[PDB]
Amino acid sequence: NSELNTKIVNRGKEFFGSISGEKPSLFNKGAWMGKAMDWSMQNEQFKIQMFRFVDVFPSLTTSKLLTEHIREYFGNEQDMPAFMAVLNKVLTSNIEEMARQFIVGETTKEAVKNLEKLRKDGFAAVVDVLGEATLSEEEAEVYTNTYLELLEALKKEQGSWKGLPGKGGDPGLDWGHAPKVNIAVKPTALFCLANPQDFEGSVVAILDRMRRIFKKVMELNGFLCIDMESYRHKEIILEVFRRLKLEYRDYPHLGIVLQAYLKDNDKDLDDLLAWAKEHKVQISVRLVKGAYWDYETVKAKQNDWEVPVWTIKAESDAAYERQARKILENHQICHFACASHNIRTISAVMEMARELNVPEDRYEFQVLYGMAEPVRKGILKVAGRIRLYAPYGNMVPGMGYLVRRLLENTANESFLRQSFAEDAQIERLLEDPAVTVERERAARAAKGLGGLPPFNNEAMVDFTRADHRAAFPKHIAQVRTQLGKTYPLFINGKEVRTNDLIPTVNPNKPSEVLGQICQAGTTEVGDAIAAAKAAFPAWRDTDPRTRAEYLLKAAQAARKRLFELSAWQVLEIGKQWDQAYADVTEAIDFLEYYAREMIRLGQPQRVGHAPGELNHYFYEPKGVAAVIAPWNFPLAISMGMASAAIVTGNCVVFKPSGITSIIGWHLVELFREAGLPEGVFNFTPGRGSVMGDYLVDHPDISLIAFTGSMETGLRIIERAAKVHPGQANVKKIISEMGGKNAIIIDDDADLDEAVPHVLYSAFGFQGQKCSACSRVIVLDAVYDKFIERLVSMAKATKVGPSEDPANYMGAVADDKAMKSIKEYAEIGKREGHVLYESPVPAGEGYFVPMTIIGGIKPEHRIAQEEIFGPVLAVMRAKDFDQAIEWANSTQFALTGGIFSRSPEHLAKARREFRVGNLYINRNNTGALVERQPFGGARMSGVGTKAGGPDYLLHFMDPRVVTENTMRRGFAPIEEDDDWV
Amino acid sequence: SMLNSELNTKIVNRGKEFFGSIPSLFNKGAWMGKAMDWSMQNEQFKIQMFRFVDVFPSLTTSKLLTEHIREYFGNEQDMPAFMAVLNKVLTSNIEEMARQFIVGETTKEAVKNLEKLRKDGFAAVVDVLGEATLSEEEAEVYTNTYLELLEALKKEQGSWKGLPGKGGDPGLDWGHAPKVNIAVKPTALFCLANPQDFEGSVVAILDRMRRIFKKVMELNGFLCIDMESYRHKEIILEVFRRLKLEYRDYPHLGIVLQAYLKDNDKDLDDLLAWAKEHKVQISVRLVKGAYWDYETVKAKQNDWEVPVWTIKAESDAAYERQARKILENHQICHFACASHNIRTISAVMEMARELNVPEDRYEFQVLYGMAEPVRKGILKVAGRIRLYAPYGNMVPGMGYLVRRLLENTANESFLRQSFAEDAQIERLLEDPAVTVERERAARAAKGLGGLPPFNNEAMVDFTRADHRAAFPKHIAQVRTQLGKTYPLFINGKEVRTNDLIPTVNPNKPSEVLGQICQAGTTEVGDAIAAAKAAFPAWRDTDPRTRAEYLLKAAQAARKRLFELSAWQVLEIGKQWDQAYADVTEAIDFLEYYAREMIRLGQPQRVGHAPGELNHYFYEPKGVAAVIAPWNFPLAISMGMASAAIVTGNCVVFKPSGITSIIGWHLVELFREAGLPEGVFNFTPGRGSVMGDYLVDHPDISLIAFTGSMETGLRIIERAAKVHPGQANVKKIISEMGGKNAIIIDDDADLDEAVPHVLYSAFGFQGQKCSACSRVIVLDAVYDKFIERLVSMAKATKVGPSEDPANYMGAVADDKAMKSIKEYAEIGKREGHVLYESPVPAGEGYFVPMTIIGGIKPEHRIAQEEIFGPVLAVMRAKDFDQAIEWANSTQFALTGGIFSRSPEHLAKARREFRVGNLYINRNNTGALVERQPFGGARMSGVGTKAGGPDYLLHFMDPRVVTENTMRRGFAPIEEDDDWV
Ligand SMILES: Cc1cc2c(cc1C)N(C[C@H](O)[C@H](O)[C@H](O)COP(=O)(O)OP(=O)(O)OC[C@H]1O[C@@H](n3cnc4c(N)ncnc43)[C@H](O)[C@@H]1O)c1[nH]c(=O)[nH]c(=O)c1N2
């Protein structure tokens, strides 16, 4: 509204006038930090080096680590900027100085002394406790107890504090109305397993500790603010606030943070206000724009979720002014904290509040300590009511906080950068951001092949959504109404029953029988092969684009049954909810990706450029493919190998693993729904001891795709190499076998990241993945600290049925797996020393304890042999060279990981840690189609990589047709001829 | 210059006297004019129509005709308005079109039609139509047709008054010219005419030409020696020179020179100087040239310099330039202007006037049936016109028709421009030198990593005197180098052993080329150890650097091309061309795999998610065993070894025993390239001693093998075993046998099918995995195809490969000879022998060139790879059975089909499922990049050497995935999916 807007702009102009050209320290080019940020803002490579250096800085605890990282990040002295061992000293002192700029102290007593100084200068505070990520219950308790310690100290001090001057109200309160003690707590720091996948358990665990802090806050009439973290926990945190508020409906000093950069926030704010009115309670909202913009955008893109934040900066500004107005209009029920360093934003709030004649006791202004100093002083002068967000504590998390402040101040879109570094025009800085949104929305208004959109991975299940959370228990119940069926063979489009039945049961509850599976003898396998062979000529002659269309239809059929198909996997093979869904999305990805790959490869290409001649190079299928599939990714890998064979023009005889035969039947259902011609896909579960060699040895098999154990894979390779009478082809092997995968934890690893990634890599789906981390190789100097945190986190996790989302892992695949794994755990406990062995539920279930064993060395059996269960070996390496040597000390080379922030060590790992899939600074499991084509060599496979652009070629053979186009002295000229 | 402008004005003005004084294909009222018009408007149609006319004379049944009509022109709705009835429509029209260009189908009709033309004031030069000469019987028929014609003409000419002239002998044409004038195609006189055997070709052609010439002289006639494709130009010049000197006083012998050849300025200068030196006179018929598209294509296919000008005006300019040179030399050189181009004719006329040339020193010639108003106008303006008049069988008459239609309707044709186009006369009569400069100026407006794009190495080119002389010289030089002992080469050191095996010349086994040290298991083990020790540093060597060694090796080989070829002539009995092609293929592999590794050597980002980088790249495997064949001893050895090496593996190489010296060439080439020690190790040895040891060794990660199915299958079976300490599952790269068929369809062009089949079967005496060992011939063309194939076979000679007069020679060694002969005997009990050549007496592993018919798919020689000069002929009842029979073996390596049926060609492309299918050419001689080579079934494991998938087989892929987000920030990368 032009009138209000003009008052806002003039208010903003006065503000800029009052500042007198002063710059915040970060933009003071006479200071070292100003120089560092100046160069960071001019040179993106330096910015990345400098900011990553500050991130790793607190782990550089020896002279050697420090000296080496300085050289690795910034180069030799002669090549550093001028503003930049004496060098160790100058860098250390300047970085520590920058971090102290944003922190009120390292101890409670220091924090308190400094806050009282702040009061004497007219500033109120909200205190925050710095901390590393909470990875255990002990860490959650230390964090909780620090707030209690802080509150007990403030309790003794606040009586001696005169209330900050206000225009009215109570002289014992700040500005006449605000409680003198105000603290902010990060909710997920109160529960190390906070996850919307276990929504209720997460709310309760956080609520219980928040309640303890809150009672102490109430005891001294203080204010508690529940801070808002990443989008993943937003709904959990809102529910925590609501419940705590209702437990103390008469206590007014409880706040929640809401983030204006979220598209959800208009609705979330309106819902919260309606909720408060409904319940006749009052609330307090600290509105911020939001702290995790880059993270949310990246995470959403990585999982093919809708980006939850606005992506044009002015949209967040516009959203802020809009939502601030809403809060102010509702000042009767909603107290407001304006949390922004943007003068336009601040000015907007001030003018809107004056216009709505909001009482001053219903709104205050807040800024981050040590930041935008002239804005802070300007707020004091014009508004009077200004509160500093004041973190205190250890320098280790202090450095992480510093990095976030540097990122915030130096961002391209940063109001502070634009005002104080870039000399932006005031009129542009102060313009209505709604106007800004239109102009940039308008400017912004300015690829696949063959009519198909490009490949994108199917969206992962998203438990921030209530509907996704509710879908699993519903679809599991539906599956339970479908139990007890008999599953026949499927050959040449018909069901063939045998009289050899094997039950398939729930590994978490073996008395629960899911169905009975018919077993194929050699007779039926031979029939299936004969059917595939008869179907092959017509299928081979089918246009590749038409073959791809069948995979696309199968993908659509699967997509429509996504939760149903997932639920079957939860019960049949003990997949956790997320593990099951990811198995189904991966199956979908293979279908979408291989369809596209066949379309790409299906067009014959001209080769050579000589005139009078046309050479066309193209591919043809081999014949009948045996597909022998594992139980651990029962839909994904089955569908991957089968659809790859099918789309390339081969016909398939498919043997699922016995214990996941129902999932294998899903391929029958999906390919039938797609209308696949009969005989192209045949489903023949059977006993390996009866028909295993028969299927592999058969003369009409031309290709064998196998995923499973090395022993079986090697046997197949040996038997398949023989050419029997009537055998048309040398048999082609496509094989992925075991791994004994290591993750290296280097001295400078970020343990906040390493610990949960190692735990998930080792124990996700009970460790039953060929990619699972079974060896964690830890550098000497960080060993004790890493292990303490790894074991403490493991202790917080629960083992139990996979249908219950509160359990981290559950039973292993079957009775034989359980016995094999337990034997390996006993072997390991005699080779090394047990560090952790979890409780398991009493009663039925193939439960193996989550097990961590230290003291492991490369000559030990559990350092060498694939266990395929929740048994983690911890190995202590004396130096990085030994770590690499130990990583490479097995006969396998499937996956590997390394957590390190040393460019030199990462480079050595890229070169020498020669696994098929090496992961840097993240878990080594969860490979995605296209992004991480999966497979290795050594004893881990034959160098074929599923989900990659070389894969389909392995299912075909190339052919060339060469035509002499010259007749009677003339040949047609072709576009690409070498001519004259 | 100023003089230039004045003469041009006279030429332009003369051009208009021709146009004022002034064909049936451009007449849009006649059916042909309509068919031609649509051909000139729609190129797709032109191609169909011309190819249809080409195949037309093979369409001998109602079924063939009807189906080809449908396949070429679509259904009676698809085809245009000027188009069973259609069968009748096309037949009469096409036959009528062909008759327009020939003066008769018999000698009597021809002679009667020539006499008509005489009374109409036209002289003639008579030519005999014929299919390609493929045998001695055919060359004799062609020869005797000329003698028969001359005998007929001899009785008529005394009755002819000479064409009216300005004076002289009234019994002679125009007072001076012989009434009888004939033209002969020299290569039609010898079915094996080939500059590779230069002297033999000259003599064989010369002997028949002399016989014709004697008869010509007996009636005081004129003999013109026509000029054919560039391949035979030097042969034909030499035939003309020898015959001329044999009858130095007889003035009525002419040669054709082609102005489209860049060589022609010098060839004409040389010929004129030659005539003055020998004090003889000559006659030249200057033409522009009949084989333009062919010469351009052929040159590009063999990486030779294109021998013709490629801007049409350059040929016109050359013609006027060369006609002037002849006319300046009119005292010694009689001139026949042979062009239908009015500018060209007017230029000759005004130059002759400018140089005051007497009329008895030049005449004008045009082809019969063509440029009638030019022949009308030239007769009236120029006065002395001779029609080139072919006569004979309708079959070659149709092929001649195709050429005339091609000439008349070419975009750059002076005739097409003059009429159908309605062009400005100013542009048509323009000095072609001015056109040249403009077009050259217009024309005055790729590789990777600084390297030129790949091109195949130029093939040996025996049109050149230096290439012809190089082989005898280099064979001699190799013979000064015999008698050496060749050691193992391990870890950069020569290692001698006490076990020596001689290598001898298969065409002369008493000639011993050297002694080869054999490696025991201990030496093999040492070489594997050396390779393994060199591997980590080699693996860590930049792909671009590794590729550089291959490029150095390729330059090293390129500098020794003739020397390297000569060793193969002597050590394994390669013919000259076969030997040189073996070395160029080796060079091609080096150049191609170097480029392929550079392309594949860069890690590529995969996926597009932000906060993440995935890089996909390749790693070598380790030690590669390379087990090489003797039949392509440099090419395939170098291909398999350089591929393994460039991809970062280290090689232990076992050459075949009988080509161990060729194996040593790899040692020499890699050493000259400076390859690091241990990366390539040379260990010849006895299979019975060290074969399994090498294959079984646990330090071996890859085996590259080319050879027999039996040995290949054993290797595959043994390598599948993982032994203690074996790091990888062994990768197999294998090319094994073939039992390759060529199908000869009913409508096949037999002039092409016959020599290509003969070459495919007996080139390098059948010792190629790609060789044709089965020719599957359609029922209705069987008897005719076999007669010509057998008759051509009979004309070839078996003997030592160092003598280029021989087609094929001795097989590889004693063992091969015994094995092949056992198969021949087996074959002769299974079928019936059609041909079995003589072979030289005395020493040498000679097996006769052998052709056997009555063969069916159940027969052993229809199934088992013989690897020798034994060709099975199989008679198929229809095309479906031909395809079935072609597919009836356990092999699928190469195959060929001669057919001009779109439907049959489509069926073959789909169903004749070999690794390399060839259409209308031989099925041998695959080239790098153009024909990546290899197959499946029992012929291999689907790896194709010389193609873009091949290097991946020697490596394994790796992916590195990095989470780039720290503390909530990640660098934005170019190809990120972002906002
Ligand atoms: C007292 C107090 C307490 C807290 C916080 C701040 C203060 C002052 N913060 C941090 C807060 O989110 C952060 O400081 C502000 O977003 C900074 O924005 P300004 O108005 O200062 O600056 P400025 O006006 O320059 O705004 C920058 C903001 O715009 C947004 N943005 C940047 N690029 C964008 C784009 N391309 N598209 C759309 N939006 C874009 C981001 O939110 C970014 O922070 C927070 N944060 C949080 O999430 N939870 C919390 O509990 C707290 N706690």
Image (cartoon, coloured by chain):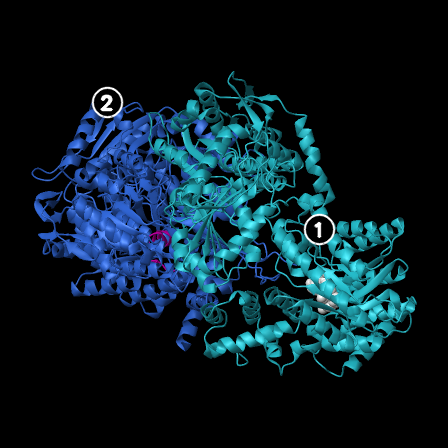
Chain colours: A cyan, B blue
Question: Which residue is pictured at 48% across the width and 30% down the height?
Answer: A816
Does residue A195 belong to the magenta stretch?
A: no
Does residue B302 belong to the magenta stretch?
A: yes
Does residue A416 appear anywhere in the picture? yes
Q: Which mark is residue B830?
A: 2
On the same chain: label 1 and label 2?
Answer: no
Q: What residue type is labelled 2?
A: Glu
The percent position of residue A947, horizontal first and vertical second, equals 51, 44
C-alpha separation, residue under disc 1 versus residue under disc 2 = 91 Å
In the visual, does B510 lie left or right of B728? left
Residue sitting nearer the eye, A241 or B778: A241
In the visual, does A770 lie left or right of B122? right
Does residue B577 appear anywhere in the picture? no
The percent position of residue A464, horizontal first and vertical second, equals 70, 47
Q: Which residue lies furthest to the front in this view?
A: A156
What SS does tag 1 mark?
A: helix
Q: Are circles 1 and 2 on residues that touch, CB within 8 Å?
A: no
10 Å crowding of disc 2: few (<14), some (14-19), many (20+): some
The percent position of residue B98, horizontal first and vertical second, equals 41, 40
Image-quarter location of ligand 1: bottom right
Is ligand 1 closer than 8 angstroms to the Cβ of mark 1? no
Question: Which residue is pictured at 64% across the width and 36% down the height?
Answer: A803
Q: Residue B362 carries which label?
A: none
Residue sitting nearer the eye, A830 or B716: A830
Residue A392 in which image quadrant = bottom right
In the visual, does A608 lie left or right of B753? right
Is ligand 1 closer than 8 angstroms to the Cβ of mark 2? no
Q: Mark 1 points at which residue?
A: A206
Range of magenta residues: B295-309
